Length: 305
Length: 161
Ligand SMILES: CC1=CC(=O)CC(C)(C)[C@@]1(O)/C=C/C(C)=C\C(=O)O
Ligand SMILES: [Mg+2]
Ligand SMILES: [Mg+2]
Ligand SMILES: [Mg+2]
Image 1 (cartoon, protein in one colour):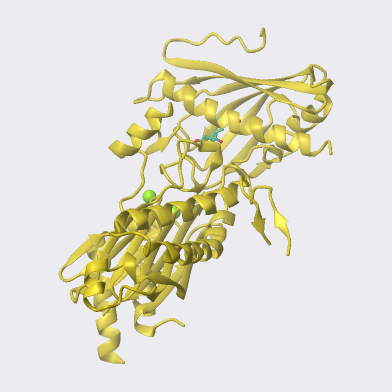
Image 2 (image 1 turned 90 degrees about the vertical axis):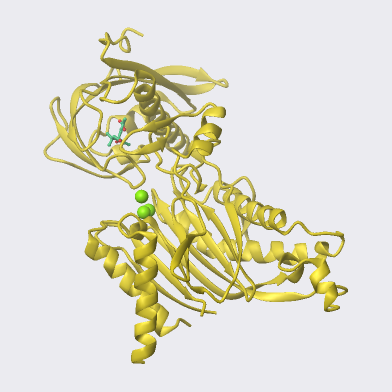
């Protein structure tokens, strides 16, 4: 329920990174968090219970910042409406496959945002727009973390990454969507595309990721379908780190976890966002700058304990 | 086709892409001929600097946007036939992997849906970089060219309404 956000253009000409932090963005149907049997054990299975959730997001735009900003402004609204609708449908199923439902709600949310970006569906601005938001070569990564009392649900689409610092060990809650992945290469080549090593493995030799919002000039090879990971919260959990590759290209998961935990503990022993988590995010950002990153850097740190 | 028939050696690749545009040829050519402003229709160009007037041998310095395998390219004007609508450009520098890249773009009249329209053809010959195949190099260049001609079509058709 507590976070900090550090974000800088860095040594770059333009700023194409965006981030979002929306507390109480939606109410999560509890049937997405606990089985009907464990809730029925407490008698909390007849009506439609809901547990408020927070949403954090990092969006690394390319070819411009319009798509990243649009994801920041729209993803939480669409996801909130989708969860609201699914709440009126979980009670009609004897047993809830929670992981498949999370995958479906995040897939439909990301696909809706992508269709709004590309202009395949209309968007509300008292007025309606139907043209694409920007050119066909503009896109953005999207990593979102839904945090609630019981679970962290991660939806990833691109090469931005989120890491859970749990105990003495970092746990990656998202796998980068680089086109050299075996399953992603198999999908792209199965659709008739190519993954070419051209200053890195790239779709058609151009884009260094296989999934993103927008980038309609590279469809159907680049898709907006996210990978979702549902992880229950434990007392080992310390913090979450959501960042663009401006941090991950120069800082590893372990170094980021130890640095963030040490900075939070240091602020607490020595002494809306949280000041300690903000100190952690700022330290991570300036550490990525010090290591030599020339990229935009965005870091959200979510203190869990 | 006499303008897009390169003679590639085995260590190189050469190809061409075409695009039909619902706009008159002198408008499309009026866009393409601006050697100093490739951002007029190239979606990947962010900045372009050129000194002096446009003439055979002029050199433009191009900076491309993010999300690409390169950042800058130095390109020289090899040919500009205003009345034949022919533009030929050679890459002479930059931080990219397109060595000895030469392209020829021609603009031709054509009737599209009963209205005046344009056929744009852009061919190229380029050295295959070490580690890549011909199919990969031609596929990458064809992808960029297809994006450029699509954008040229959209800007040209938006300038008719
Ligand atoms: C978009 C981009 C990516 C690269 O990796 C090379 C380079 C920087 C040259 C380029 O501008 C390529 C431009 C090409 C092929 C054609 C053109 O636009 O006439
Ligand atoms: Mg970017
Ligand atoms: Mg990277
Ligand atoms: Mg980046």
